[PDB]
Image (cartoon, rainbow, N blue to C red):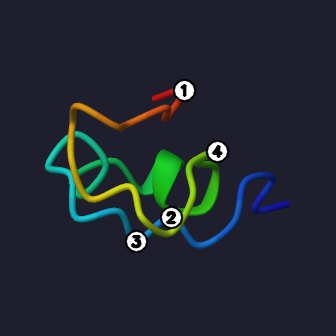
Amino acid sequence: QNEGHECQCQCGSCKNNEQCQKSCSCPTGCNSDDKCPCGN
């Protein structure tokens, strides 16, 4: 499915890969590379 959730993380590292967009494992707060726990 969208095995993560709606990522929407304002991190460039997120905001590029539609993989993480739906398959990201970060909290809503993740809008900073510093605090990007994303497995993509």
**Among the two numbered marks 2 and 1 on one chain, the one whose residue lies closer to the N terminus:** 2
C-alpha distance separating marks 4 and 1: 7 Å
Q: Where is residue 12 in the image (x, y as percent from the top left)?
A: 14, 49
- Examine the image and state in which quarter residue 8 appears: bottom left
The label number, if any, that marks residue 26 in the structure image: none
Determine which residue is flagged by label 4: 25
Q: In this view, does 13 lie above or below 4?
A: above
The label number, if any, that marks residue 39 in the structure image: 1
Determine which residue is flagged by label 2: 7
Q: Contact (CB < 8 A) between labels 4 and 1?
A: yes
Q: Is residue 13 left or right of residue 7?
A: left
**Among the two numbered marks 4 and 1 on one chain, the one whose residue lies closer to the N terminus:** 4
The label number, if any, that marks residue 8 in the structure image: 3
- Examine the image and state in which quarter residue 5 appears: bottom right
C-alpha distance separating marks 2 and 1: 11 Å
Q: Between residues 5 and 17, which one lies in front from this camera angle?
A: 5
For the residue labelled by badge 1, is the local secondary structure a helix, a strand or a loop? loop
Q: Contact (CB < 8 A) between labels 4 and 3?
A: no
Which residue type carries mark 1? Answer: Gly
Q: Position of residue 38 (x, y in %)?
A: 49, 35
Q: How crowded is mark 2: few (under 14 residues within 10 Å), some or many (20 or more)?
A: many
For the residue labelled by badge 3, is the local secondary structure a helix, a strand or a loop? loop
C-alpha distance separating marks 4 and 3: 11 Å
Q: Is residue 20 above or below residue 9?
A: above
